[PDB]
Image: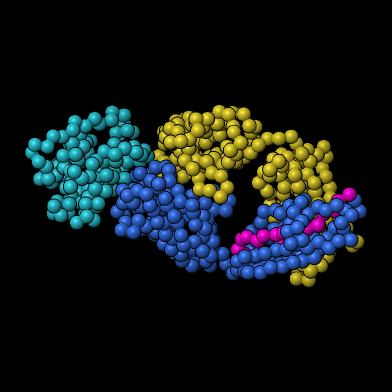
Amino acid sequence: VRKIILELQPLSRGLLEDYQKKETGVPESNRTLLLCLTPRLNSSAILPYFRAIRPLSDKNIIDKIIEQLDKLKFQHEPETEISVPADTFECKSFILTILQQFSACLESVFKSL
Amino acid sequence: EIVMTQTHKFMSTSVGDRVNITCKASQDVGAALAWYQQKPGQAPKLLIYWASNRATGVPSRFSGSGSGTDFTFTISSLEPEDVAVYYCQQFSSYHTFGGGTKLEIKRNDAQPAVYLFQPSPDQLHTGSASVVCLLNSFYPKDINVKWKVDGVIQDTGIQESVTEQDKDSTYSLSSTLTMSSTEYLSHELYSCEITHKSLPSTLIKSFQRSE
Amino acid sequence: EVQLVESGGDLVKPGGSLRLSCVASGFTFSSYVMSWVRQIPEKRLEWVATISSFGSYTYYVDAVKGRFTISRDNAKNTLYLQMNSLRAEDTAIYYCTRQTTMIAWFAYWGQGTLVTVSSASTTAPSVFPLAPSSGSTVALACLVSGYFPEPVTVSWNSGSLTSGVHTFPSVLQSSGLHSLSSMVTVPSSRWPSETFTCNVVHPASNTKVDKPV
């Protein structure tokens, strides 16, 4: 479990910082999207969001993230179907909030361990 | 670098009136503009982003419009708590701010009370001489104070200090002419000459040093 | 609630250094871009520097490049501004701000910390009484000359005289010292039969003067 956190952390940090550098004027969504814990890390609550933004992001990093989180998922656990905002500004806020909360979850879980 | 121009440093408005504050960008910024309000002693507060989105909790009388290079911040009906400085800011590229537009309350014209003070003997002992012209409780803000020593207009040695709009909407201002004590002692007639909308002709306050 | 608290502003000489800190609470600090904005005494705003979540990317305004360094310590929820080779025009209130990406607007501001760069050392004011040059009223004044740093407080007759007092805003002289004037209008019966005094306090130099007019 510490192993998956450490594998994911550079991927998450890079995705967030690259978005902060490339995207200008992204509004605050004020939404909670990712549920960090279940109490173990909550792959089934986090995974659908990454599946939903895969076409909008770096598919290669996303695929690595998904492969890591799949290892922390019960096969029986169902995944919510995610609604990605269609409006361009809402869609960037949606992506940005996912990256922020994923970063925060891993940092939180790491302090736990 | 994208230069943001607010043409008016100050605007006079009346409570209940519509206020239009303009901001123009030197190049296209699209809609990537923000508006801030600042009151004395506080940080700026975000009001509008993406040129027209009102931030959470911002009163509905505030609004923004424009896209491209020309932007307008609008208060539909000015309220007394709206007296403040408003700044635009573009985030198309590296952050730049407009220079600010101070809103103040329009009132009836008011004539200045003018007082003129000679340098005190204690100051002259140190080698300097400050001649002090003090103007109290005038409206409007725009005023012209001219200094003449033995009839020649001075263009150096003059510091001006204007107050903020006081509680009854009038302004006060100081103008001080500083020179060496020897230079002060070489002249006789010191005049502070005031031109202002409320005065039908220039008000001259003067004194003769040799008295 | 989101809170940003700046500290470390102080007086310094040109060419000196100073380190500002901003401690943040109420949000996950490492999720956000952080920035400094300053406001000079003429009240123009100027963006200063910006740092991404984990410090990989930084931007600086040209005026401070090669003199200032922005950095952050995510463990301590702290943003820093290391300021070197300070100049007089660096004098400003420095605000810590939070942003979503590196180029955006500023929705959250701290209260600011004042940085004053001046070649003048702390200087006590000289207080010069300005007596009238007959009437219903007369005007008395005090020139509070050449002090640093701001502010002074001026009162009249140990504060008993408040009506008709007018203290003007201070102006900065090329020497780096400030001056202002204070005046009062009194009923003409009260002068010159009574004595009037202006009381000037300069906290920074811990000096108190009473000058009779």
Residue B51 visible, this orientation: no
**Chain B drawn colour:** yellow
- Residue at x 74%, y 54% (from the top left corner): C162
The answer to whether residue B186 is above or below residue B60 is below
For residue B49, what is the image quadrant?
top left
Looking at the image, residue C84 lies above or below residue B145: below
Residue C70 rendering spot, x and y as whole percentages: 38, 57
User: Chain A: what color?
Assistant: cyan
- Residue A33 located left or right of residue C210: left
Find chain C in the image and tell me its colour.
blue
x, y percent for residue A97:
29, 41
What residue appears at the point 87 percent right and 58 percent down from the top-left corner? C191
The percent position of residue C136, horizontal first and vertical second, equals 89, 49
Q: Residue at x 31, y 43 (%)?
A: A22
In this view, the residue in front, C178 or A42, is A42
Q: Nearer the viewer, residue C68 or B182?
A: C68
Which of the two residues, B112 or C163, is positioned nearer the viewer here? Answer: C163
Label the magenta part by its dominant secondary structure: strand
**Is residue C182 in view?**
yes
Question: Which residue is located at x 50 percent, y 33 percent?
Answer: B59
Magenta residues, as a range? C136-155
Q: Is residue C72 magenta?
A: no
